[PDB]
Image 1 (cartoon, one colour):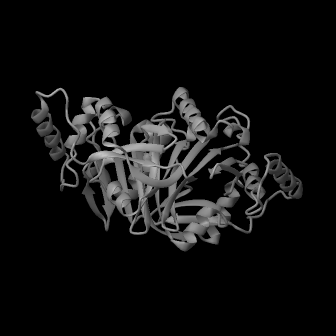
Image 2 (tube, each protein chain N blue to C red):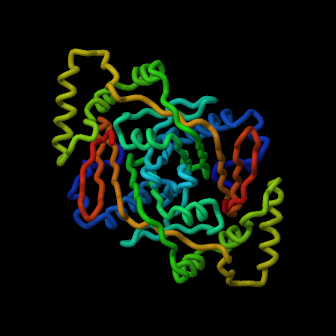
Image 3 (cartoon, helix red, strand yellow):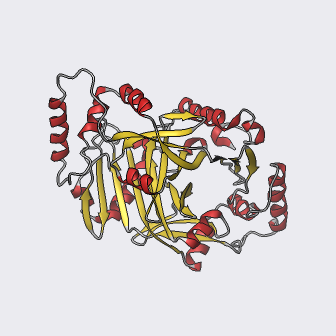
Length: 203
Length: 203
């Protein structure tokens, strides 16, 4: 009970729909000092087996949750074969989690440009520096990669989008809010087809 | 490079094997005040589609990472059909991640007893109060479930293991260490067939 300082998560918390509540939860985490409050752990499937890693949620609206990545990465390939994902926001400090699962689609060239342009150039370089799946043996080699990319763009103030870099967006088909409680009787609300369902703590 | 106070993770950080490094990283997460240092996001598969939620890693050894849960949860059913998982320790505050993927076996009845007994009275009751199927319409109902189970065991000093309750272990067939860097030239070392491998940041 203590952890988020709040009373029980219940149906009425969803009165303004799933989006308002997620946006509020994401803001409580930001405000409470959580590091990377917008990071989520994304699961995809590779040859029938699940694979997990962390990505940064950059857009949240009625169409779902979006993040940015190289199309050439393993996440990209896996999502190309099996375009469904699940993501979890792990807000342990507050005893909270939210999960989103659904079909994945690419974001617009439009949107890619915008979020690419807000990117601090320290990172713009970094993106370009990552030599998509090129063999690497040392760390020095990584350094050379970033030096080489840095020179190449030194006289450019408007670094362009790499040829295979864009985003993906998970549709909010199933969204679950999880509020933990000291006496293990966790509050679990699942949203699906505009219907709401309360789940037993142990699933 | 800031976030864990450290230089680059490299092959020499693996000299005494993945187990020892995962243990060091878990411990660093503790010393730093990270909430739920041992929690991990577990992905499973449900009819070819990934599914995520957090579990607590309670055993870390040579045979892999283990957590405890009701066999009758969605996660248990999913692991029964497709006994492979991936898990991620999201240490965002230190800019670190560890991933572990592999086949999944049940823990023994021996170890279930041992870890069950280490739970405080509150958590054992909590676990017994989660009634596997039974739909839930109100939150007051969870309360009465905890109150039935409290009264039912009022005279038992030592509460028994619930009938459906046990553990799962992920074998360390792939282990990745991820250490973020301000310049985006993240360090990534994957472990597989005792062979080490540096990966390009952008996967």
